Every structure is written in structure tokens, then in C-alpha cells.
Image (tube, rainbow, N blue to C red):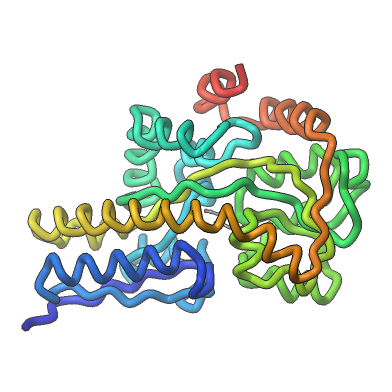
Length: 300
Ligand SMILES: O=C(O)[C@@H](O)[C@@H](O)[C@H](O)[C@H](O)CO
């Protein structure tokens, strides 16, 4: 019937990735729930803008939605808790934290300090370090140039481990690797696949150094303009999308390693104890006082 608005939703994954399918599902559900009054347009591959630029856009009123996680720590320090190295044990553990009182505090700080509102969370597979030569322990890094996302805690940890990390937008990584500006990066298998890093990296080192969740978010200024009924529809659509997305994540766990191996990547077993000990020390040396007690709890 009527179409009142179109929400623009940007993310960094490609069209086969769980996040994209979930974003599309969110849009379908929201359209149904609002009789088409609210449409969603999904922009994959950072085509709407790079993550940090989208967060700024949401604050300014030019972007409606994005999928964002621990890069929010640049505004809301508690958001670093989404992705503390070696802190979370499993999907079930992260679900408990993200949905519990600590998760509520994180959500509220993101709303207040970043002016974006989490409406769903997606748990992720573990991040792994990719490289041009095998990296079996921190001692192998030896100053290796690598990319991290715009996450100060990751700069701190990877520098302490012996690498030379540089923050960069996700969509810049492939070309930077191709051109030899960096030799490695780190991400879950789903994103290594999404961005075709198999074409520019030889090794997946099984560091499994971060298990994290990420948020589907809406600009607080967009949320504020919605009627209570439409707010409810947004939440309902997001919950449906979250349930759907978890299934897609689980499917990806069964397939992505095999896929990447079929594209020539070599998976490398690491000295997990050495990585974990060095990374936990680095986290504790660099963690904000605000979240230190929670991190110590997780590490206990
Ligand atoms: O490497 C990346 O850019 C991605 O994995 C992001 O999802 C990243 O985790 C961001 O920091 C999330 O806010």
C-alpha cells in the first residue's frame, strides 16, 4: 500500500555470508510486519560506506543501520567486551553474556555514547590469523606487518604479541595484502571466505584468538522517530533474523574450513598455550579499568 520510509543497512560481508542473508530476512520480516510501510535496502561489501564511516553517519542522521561490534569501543568502552581475546568459550557462553545484565550495560552505553541501538546480536566463529608464512607461536611474528580492524584493544594485543598491526577498513584489506603492504590479517573463517583472502594469503593459523558477537544496529535518531508499534516491529523482525542467522552460522562452521582448503589454504596448528598466555597478559596490561573486573572474571 503505502511506503513511508526505506532504511539503508550496510555491512562488510558478501552476498553469500550469513550476515547478508540475515539482513535480507530482517527486511522481509519488517516489511511484512508493517504492511510494506518500512522497507530495508541492504548494502553488502561496504558499498554504503566503511564501518567507522557508517557509525559516524548514524550519528549524523545519514545512515540508518549497520552490523557493528567491538569497533564501537571507540565511543563506548564497554563494547570492547564483545571481543576480548580468549575470554569466551563457546556460542552458549556468549549468548549468556550478550543477553544478560552485562550485555544490557553494554547496550545502554552504546546507545548513550555511540547513538546507535543494538537490536539483535549474532555470535561469530573464532578469529584466526592468516599469513604468507606459517605462524605457530607469538615468537614467529617477528614484527610481521598485519591489519586489524579499528579496534584499539586488537592493536594493543597484536603489538604486544610481536606483530606490527595497522588498523584499516575491512574492504581495503584484500588489496593491501595483494600489494604487500601487509602480510597478514585476522578474522573468522566466514569473512576470510567472504573477502576471498585465499587469493592473497597462504595460511590460516588456528589461533582462535577471539570468539565474539556483533550487533545489528539502528541509528538512535531513526529509532526515536518510529512509533511504538513500529519499534516493536523492528524488534520482532530482528529477533526472527537472529534466529535465522544462528542456523546459517552453524552451517558455515561445518563447511568453511573445507572450502578454504579447497581454495589452497593451509591450516596450521599453533602453540595455543603460548598464544593464550601472551594474549591474556597483553589484555590485562591494556584493558580499560571500566571493564577490567569483568575481564578478570572471564579469565578466572
Ligand atoms: O575485521 C573486520 O573488520 C570485521 O571482522 C569486523 O566485523 C570487526 O570485527 C569489527 O571490529 C566489528 O565492529
